[PDB]
Amino acid sequence: DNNVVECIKEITESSRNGKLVFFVGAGVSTLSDYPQWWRLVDKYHEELYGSPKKGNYSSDEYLRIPQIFYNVKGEMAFDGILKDFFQVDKPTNPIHDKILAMNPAHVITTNYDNLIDTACWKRGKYFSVISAEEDVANATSSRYLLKVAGDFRKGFKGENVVLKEDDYLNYDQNYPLISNLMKTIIATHTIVFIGYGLGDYNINMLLNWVRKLQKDSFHKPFFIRTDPSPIENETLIYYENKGLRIIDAASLIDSNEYDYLERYSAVMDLLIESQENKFITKDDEVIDYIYGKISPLFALQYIRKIDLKHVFEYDYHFEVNGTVVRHKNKGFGYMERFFELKESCDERSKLSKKQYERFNALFNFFEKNGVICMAKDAGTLNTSIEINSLAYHGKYDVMKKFIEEQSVSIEDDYKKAFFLACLGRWEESYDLYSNIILNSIDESNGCVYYLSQINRYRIYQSITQAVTQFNGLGLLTFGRHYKPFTDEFLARIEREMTNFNIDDLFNGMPFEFQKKYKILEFLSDNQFLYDDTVKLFELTNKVRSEMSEGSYSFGMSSDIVVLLRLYDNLRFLYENCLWSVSFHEFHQYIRNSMSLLIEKAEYERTRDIDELGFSFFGKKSGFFMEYYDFVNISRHFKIDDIKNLERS
Amino acid sequence: DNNVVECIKEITESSRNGKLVFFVGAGVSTLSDYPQWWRLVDKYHEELYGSPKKGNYSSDEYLRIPQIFYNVKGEMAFDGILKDFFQVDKPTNPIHDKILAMNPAHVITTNYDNLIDTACWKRGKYFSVISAEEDVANATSSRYLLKVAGDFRKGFKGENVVLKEDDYLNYDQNYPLISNLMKTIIATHTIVFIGYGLGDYNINMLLNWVRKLQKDSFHKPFFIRTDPSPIENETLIYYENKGLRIIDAASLIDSNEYDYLERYSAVMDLLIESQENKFITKDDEVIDYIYGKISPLFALQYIRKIDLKHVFEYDYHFEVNGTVVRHKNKGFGYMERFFELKESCDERSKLSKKQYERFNALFNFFEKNGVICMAKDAGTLNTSIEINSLAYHGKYDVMKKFIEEQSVSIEDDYKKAFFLACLGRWEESYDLYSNIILNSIDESNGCVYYLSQINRYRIYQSITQAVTQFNGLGLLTFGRHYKPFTDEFLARIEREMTNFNIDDLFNGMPFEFQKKYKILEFLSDNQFLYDDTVKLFELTNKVRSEMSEGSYSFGMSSDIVVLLRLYDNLRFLYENCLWSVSFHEFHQYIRNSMSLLIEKAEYERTRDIDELGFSFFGKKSGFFMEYYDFVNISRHFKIDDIKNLERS
Amino acid sequence: MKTVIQDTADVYFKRKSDGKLVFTAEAQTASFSQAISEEKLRGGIGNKPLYILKSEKEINLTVKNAFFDLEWLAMTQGSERYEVEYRTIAYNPDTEEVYSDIYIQFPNVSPSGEFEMSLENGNALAPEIKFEALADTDTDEMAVVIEASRD
Amino acid sequence: MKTVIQDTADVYFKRKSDGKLVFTAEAQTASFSQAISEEKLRGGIGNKPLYILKSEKEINLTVKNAFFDLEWLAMTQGSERYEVEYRTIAYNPDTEEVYSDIYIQFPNVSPSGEFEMSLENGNALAPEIKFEALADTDTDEMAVVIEASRD
């Protein structure tokens, strides 16, 4: 039915970002064969007289009988009976394993036992058990295990866990902060109940008053009903206009009136479904979801290949050769479907303009990178190497001419900031990124905001590093203390950057950012080089020890993937126009890469060939260096390669 | 003033723990040329009676007169004056940045203007600014901006603003969600007041509201007294009795009455400039500061001094052999005093019995951690690389006897589990780790817990790396398939793997561990090796440039460096009883520098001395086959490496 | 287009005295080795030999792209030393057309690879294998190369 | 107490034409590089050349210092023949006693600093300084040593 699938899909989507809190009701405790208050009021009535009242007690008798018993007999007898009743120790039941398996964030309980805490204990997560008004002020974590009702950790006495109707009268006057945090959690997260009927008038009146405050902006929590008998439609509409969303287990499974725990089993079975890729079976819906994912980053014009797997949650392992392979895809072949659609024009003609509007968008950057097919049927591949980075082209006059040009729009402002940084002077560059941060939210452009964060960060890093360089060193070198920056500028930048560290730069941004920009976070932290150089220094010895006795083929030997990643990550920052294009990391990367190229070439060149050494690859790539490589040598090369690699 | 001393000490406490949230006041908002409220009151009087009040307005009149204006003309001219007097942009003040410099948990805004929004947006964080009932619900982010005064982002209408007498009359229902979340924010985090006036005293109402029953679990917030007139002892007495901590700006330093800027800035920069150590003063506070941090350091077995992350929040740099270089020192040198007390004998007797015992323990631990002396007095030192091992050498009978007994402490069970796992008996290891995780919950010793947990994932990762080619490669090598595991164990391990990961292991542990055991973050990711590999490669290329040049290097520029890092890595993951020694090319991480240290001395056995080789180093350092070198050989040796080092 | 070297090479096996066909195909690694080493094992003789041509030989062979097979795997789930054949295509630099093929085969091969990788970060399978080409005492063995392009 | 052994060194600078005192407390790396080489510098005419003595002689110095001197640094804030005088000691393996001191002096050193310590993370300062050996046209210079092992 539409309502039930809608409800479960709501639960899943809210959980995916981690906004779920589960109301531990008393039903779970009695699900563990724990005797209830039914047994607990008995001896009270027996000392009262010698016979339980036939029929169901009203909402007042249940609270008043222990009150009468206490006020008549004594607190000492009250606590003694509390010991005689609350000393039972029981194991867990599969309910707790499930409810923890839902990966909650916060836990609140009203049943007065401690079974959920020990279920967490075995499960191995950390929670803060708060049960006294003084526990709140010393919160030892950001996860809170509230117990509004209170536990018996500090004993079995009245301060402890109480069910005295006088204490029902004593409201928040005892425990104000508990109610405060209860209202807070009910307000921030989406709420689900479990293990309760309709016998807590208090909670419903809280909810009704809450909905009376928020007016029409109230997030309706969810409720589960375990009645074998059906709940009538008028009651459902009453609770709907009440503000509660009921999910009825009766419409889901069929059982006996005394089945009990097997209904809860089923309701957790309903909850536990948590997936997205399992609903991709339609040919069109493949491209529908694909577009819905890929679209937000049109502002970026290129992405890295082995980086690209980060978007797709590692479901496919993207070989840098432009071909893709399955990594964690347990469902339909949506990339296999897309690649078989690519080579079939008749299937391309079986689509409307609704998908053509997204095919047009895909085309541009998809072929800009150059992904072809999978690794199975692929034949002879070939990548395109070209650089439009004029800053890489070493023509500063034209960039000055473009700098003198006025402003057009946000993307153009980003490019101009990139060239201003390219000239070396930074004052007006920082001013420009300042204004662009001011007005970026006016256009509400997501990716460029974080790109600009990284911009201003690495600009400041470069300025301060150069300052440390002129800091001392300059006087001895240039003879005069050249001060190219006003002391006011330094004072301002230092006063606005006392504490800023980049680690939380991905933690303080709106949570809607990462869901569409998971891949791009890797450019913030110091991992700008760790993911790259590892494979470089692996393949280095790989080929160096491959040596000249085998591991032999014409176009799979040695640097095959090396050129792929080499010119794939070459223009990544060099075409998106990011800034640390002058950093010893790229000195390092280019020098290593170029050395591997020359090494494979000249180890092919002079290798001894008995009969089969030259039968394989009876042609050589010879390392025919291109203009790009020469510019690399000009820019980021100190040995420049022969300076040591001619003695060696 | 000693009072001021513990106040600043506790501000430093709340500075980093994340317990701090600010309550911004009207003084700073006025400090931005923002037209004050009394001027709008005068304008209201002018448009109402055409005459100004002679004498100061009463407390009610300020919000009372606007009721008259609203009632007699109407909201037409009300919104007209809203337009006319609140459509004025203003330039920002430095107080905003100074406040945000400390990164508070949230901001409570009693100002209509969005200046706080400007400061926050150019700071770098986006806060979920809340102003109405609709605003709480859609809050996606976890960091909030709280404008109790309200904003004008919803337009220049009196409905959204809280400047109406009926509103303070009806605040209890119109905007209750913000009120309750405000109370919670007060409760769960420390509070400081800034720039707050003396007209309505939000302190008055809220202090009364929470004092209503605040028994013993409240941390009184701290108010900076801003007006030029000095505070009175009677006034301070009244307020402290009331529940506020009042610090007078003139109680530190005095200037002109209208010079609010210099006063407030002086107070706030006094409070800020304390980094971590400026009030230690005498020697009694020398011992306790290092005490509270290094007391947990006695728990662990052996630590790489490269792993000395933030011993003192990155205050000082601890290099290879064990000397100290000041990294972030500006105040008291609390390490030189302790080290010289270690150097001196008579001054040791100044320590009391407990103090002397702690000093003896600290000196012993410094002996056991390889730290000897600072570079200030570092001379001819020698550190013991005598490896302490039982499985790294292979005395299998020792653990085969060490297993057959009943343990007493959890540490015994931990080391037994590690030893047994090293033996290949990986089945009962899971049940044992279960026993530790289950029983080690009601106890305050968590490093063992963390390491126990991180074993699980790595061992299971190895096991999963095994079974696939056990049903694969298995018949490729030894022909006959085998089943070292049952189906129930496979089902249980798959079930536990399904809803588990490693990314949140550190985030899953309490705050106290995160403070005391913050170094233990690096090892439980995977790229650690990935991250020290790049350091090793930089060292590799430096050493190989040295060999290609032949450059003489004085002292400790030895690939020993390299190889002493080799011992560091070969000791760390072993002494702590961690399976993490048994991984993938960890082996090749050994291998590269292993064959490399062969090549370094191999080429090095050619030194073409000219004038300085004999004089500087007669009886040269000499390459000798180390015993630990041989253990490396017989613990890691493949065959291909032998081949290439043979032909090399 | 600009600068990348590309071909393909497959990896095929079989079983001696059997029609069992279960192994990885099309390994991008398909790595191989050859070596001839000599040592001081003849430093002393009766001073009247003819020759022995000892010539210690060494042959590694490693292939890795997984997905061996599922049928013969299932049949064997319930020591002939196998047999291996290799195929490589050589292109003419002057004409650049598919005209020539290279055939490689070894009678005996021993897959002897280490059985403990256990990488922390879960790879895409990647069960790398290595092989040693064995030789009997009768004759032949090693490599039988057949040259195509009989045009 | 096993073999974590190591020594220390002293580095002294000086500015010529006056008694300026500049020095370095310690030099950890202290990478000393000496290069002698030649490629081709002879035409080969005039029948008997009667002479050739070309020899590329370069001396490289490298120190790391955290002690400049404010006495002059502050005054300059509001060149000279940095000439360098290295100082060190030597030990006799037979006795292992402090008996010999070794001095190394350069009267003409011009610092050749590279303005590219562009790095992401904040290091422990460590401003490594690299020097070049400069020579005049008159005579001598380069290196001078003093021996203090008299007994």
Image (spheres, coloured by chain):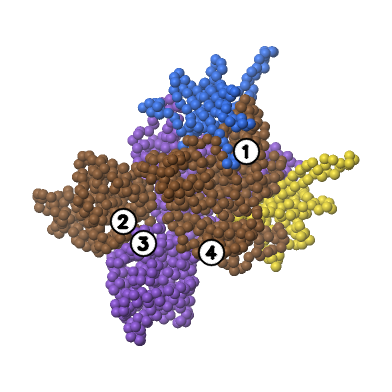
Chain colours: A purple, B brown, C yellow, D blue
Q: Are marks 4 and 3 on the same chain?
A: no
Which type of secondary structure does the marked residue at label 4 adopt? Answer: helix
Q: Earlier in the sequence, mark 3 or mark 1?
A: 3
Disc 3 from disc 1: Cα separation: 67 Å
Q: Are marks 4 and 3 in contact (CB under 8 Å)?
A: no
Q: Chain of mark 4?
A: B
- Amino acid type indicated by mark 2: His
Q: Chain of mark 1?
A: A
Please state, as top left, top right, bottom left or bottom right, where the C terminus of chain A lies in the image.
Answer: top right
Which type of secondary structure does the marked residue at label 3 adopt? Answer: loop
Q: Which residue is mark 1?
A: A598
Q: Which residue is mark 4?
A: B434
Disc 4 from disc 1: Cα separation: 55 Å
Q: Which mark is residue B219?
A: 2
Q: Chain of mark 2?
A: B
Q: Chain of mark 3?
A: A
Which residue appears at 40% of the width and 29% of the height? D70
Number of other residues with Cα within 10 Å of mark 1, as a class: few under 14, some 14 to 19, many 20 or more: some
Disc 4 from disc 2: Cα separation: 40 Å
Q: Which residue is mark 3?
A: A135
- Amino acid type indicated by mark 4: Ser
